[PDB]
Image (cartoon, coloured by chain):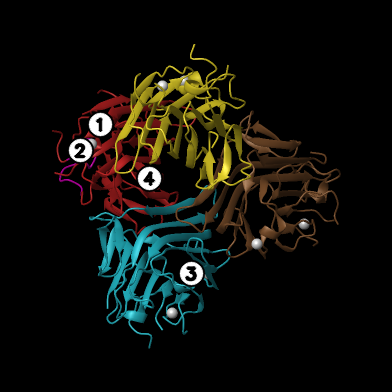
Chain colours: A brown, B yellow, C red, D cyan
């Protein structure tokens, strides 16, 4: 299977409450935190990591609201391949709901032992268009809808994904400090008062694709909840 | 053929080394005298913005001269909406190298609405053996000293960034890009025929047949 | 007097219409363009310059609207001192109105002839606070009001200014390419249908202060319309 | 006294050269063994973010070792809201230099609302004679090779950035900073007593009386 490191936001029953979690190759989060999923409101996720601290951290917030944060000491050099692809995933249950990404930005940096040796990548979407050639859209994912990214069909069990086209060089054996930082504003709107949903920022192998039966709780990242 | 907009640095015998702006033709739309310094590391600065509709480049060497060349052009009319950026190089009958020590790019689409910036930005300061985010064409290679060797070390090589770039948009108030790269042309011969170039092309541009020498690996014919 | 290079947006009668203009040491713009001042709506100004082109350019736009642009070939090396301070200015006439700056960002870069020799400065305000120590507030200018910058009193003839604390190194004799880029979102709200107002992004000597009698058409930048 | 948070690199005889994190005291809260390489250019990387509340530094030399030292600390409780950042240095009885070749900083305040980022970012790659955006204290100077000479070329010098920095805010979901600088300590003596440090202090911090030698120009007494 694919190598997945993710930061999911799910409201599925399958802890008995909405949470934010850090998944290292398994849907069974290595660490979680209570999340107050606010239907209709726009939320913001901040994911960060640096090779010095070897600590992955995320923070989800809503305006005038709470903020769920979850960290996990992990050396991605041991988990992920050298070259990866980053993305966003989403899955819907039996509920009518949307997983709209309003914005998305990423920054990766490899700093070598030598002088002025920085290597970086940085994309920043604040408006998706109909023909977004720099995004690999998988599943029921689409663009252009209000200049937004619709991960799940805009709905009865839907799984969508959107990874950036260019492969990302997460780590290097010669780097003194490698680090990344992602951010995205979402909006989960559902008519139902308590929908089962799930978004996630994931890092995977350059050729990761939706596993068969990765629906619902599997977030489109895992083929089974092993 | 492919749609090419380039900023070349050639020493192929106007009757002298120059820096030029090519719009779909190897016959530069505008040039400037360039003092090609063999062995020394040079720096190219290419810039453009939709407001000014003026493409400009500046090549310099440390403690040296600086050739600059600008050209009023609306790339919205020349280039497709989605492109791929890159570096090209070709050698003549001479023993020489076209080593890219560094390369960075920045593209920005600013919409009419509030806080609506879209951007892309890569920065190579050290190329590795397996550079998956670069499409290497021709005799181009990586890892050699953590550098990019465009030509074989009559050679022709290319290196384009993997992700397609969104140069323009009909809804943007201001689109702009900025590239920079440090080169080093070393040749045993005192007066070699060489040529590097920063080019913007269609996402699927490939080395045209017979685009050797003066054609810079960008054009199939000068006519 | 002070050395002023500015990009003003005025609706004063004193051409016979609202315009956007480039001022080089004189209130009498060196170049202007028709501006459709939209009362109540938030506008965005984009000012840019680079030593290669020696061309100053500005672009003002409103959402779903028009866009006034004005350029002017000028070598700031000959006009401005090496070290300057950047800022925003505003003045009100006999009208009740506001000059609210919602955001402001600047980027200055000095690139030398040598390798990897970039020098830069970059600030970005998206929310002003009550105690904004990194801003020199002159005139009736204030902060904190909604986390915004109120240039003119929030009004019967008011002149305010706000310059960044750190001096900016615009040019250098040893640089191959110097360049700057500023952006700011404004909002001019007036009860009157046709108010006389004026905002401006200005570059001046590190110790520039509101000239005596620089009210109204003088934009708080010039002591007299010479 | 002033409020000082610093990341020092001293060779003043623990009984060996080290890299340390000082929170209001010269007696480091955490240290690590540092192989001070005389003559060679080193690079310090200091980072911090409000989520992790962990200050970390990493010092390296080309083709060399790398000393790293981290310390869990909430700067919201230590530092004032508005500060000034800088570099400090002190020499012992030895003939030596404390040359800063480059220096860059980035501070970011991200609010709970949408697209609410506030940032500051300076980047010196070449200091000039009249560097108006730097507050030079002590024997500190600029222009020498387009470099920053902290100590006299028992010296003590400092260089803080002019604009006050807004480290934290009560309304921010995530605040963070990142500094980097390349130094070069050259000494004729094989084992000199020296010390550089990146420090964060109150906007009006000045060299304390008798903050020489081991005190790094930051503290008036070690007690
Ligand atoms: Mn879960
Ligand atoms: Mn590892
Ligand atoms: Mn030519
Ligand atoms: Mn056009
Ligand atoms: Mn006017
Ligand atoms: Mn000049
Ligand atoms: Mn110590
Ligand atoms: Mn605190």
Asked if labels 1 and 3 touch by Cβ distance under 8 angstroms, the answer is no
Q: Is residue A163 left or right of residue D62?
A: right
Is the C-beta of the residue carrying label 3 under 8 Å from the nearest atom of ligand 8? yes
The prevailing secondary structure element of the residues shown in magenta is loop
Q: Quadrant of ligand 7?
A: bottom left
| Residue toward you, B144 or C5 | B144
Counting other residues with Cα less than 10 Å from the Cα at mark 1, is it few (<14), some (14-19), or many (20 or more)?
Answer: some
- Label 2 – label 3 distance at C-alpha: 44 Å
- The residue labelled by disc 4 is C106
Pointer 1: what residue? C74
Name the residue that disc number 3 marks: D76
Q: Which mark is residue B148?
A: none
Q: Is residue C219 part of the magenta span, yes or no?
A: yes
- At horizontal 59% and vertical 49% (from top left) the residue drawn is A183
User: Around disc 2, counting alpha carbons within 10 Å, would you say few (fewer than 14), some (14 to 19), or many (20 or more)?
Assistant: few
Chain letter for mark 2: C
């Amino acid at each position: 299977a694919d190598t997945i490191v993710a930061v999911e936001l799910d409201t599925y029953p399958n802890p008995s409450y909405p949470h934010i979690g850090i998944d290292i190759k398994s849907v069974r989060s290595k660490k979680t935190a209570k999340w107050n999923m606010q239907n209709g409101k726009v939320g913001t996720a901040h994911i960060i990591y640096n090779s010095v601290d070897k600590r992955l951290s995320a923070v989800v917030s809503y305006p005038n609201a709470d903020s769920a944060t979850v960290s996990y000491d992990v050396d991605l050099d041991n988990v992920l391949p050298e070259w990866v692809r980053v993305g966003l995933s989403a899955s819907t249950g039996l509920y009518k709901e949307t997983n709209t990404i309003l914005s998305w930005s990423f920054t990766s940096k490899l700093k070598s032992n030598s002088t002025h040796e920085t290597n970086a990548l940085h994309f920043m979407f604040n408006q998706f268009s109909k023909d977004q050639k720099d995004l690999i859209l998988q599943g029921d994912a689409t663009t252009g809808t209000d200049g937004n990214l619709e991960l799940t069909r805009v709905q009865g069990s839907s799984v969508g994904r959107a990874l950036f086209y260019a492969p990302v060089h997460i780590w290097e054996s010669s780097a003194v400090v490698a680090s990344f930082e992602a951010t995205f504003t979402f909006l989960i709107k559902s008519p139902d008062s308590h929908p089962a949903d799930g978004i996630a920022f994931f890092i995977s192998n350059i050729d990761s694709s939706i596993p068969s039966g990765s629906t619902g709780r599997l977030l489109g990242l895992f083929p089974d909840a092993n």
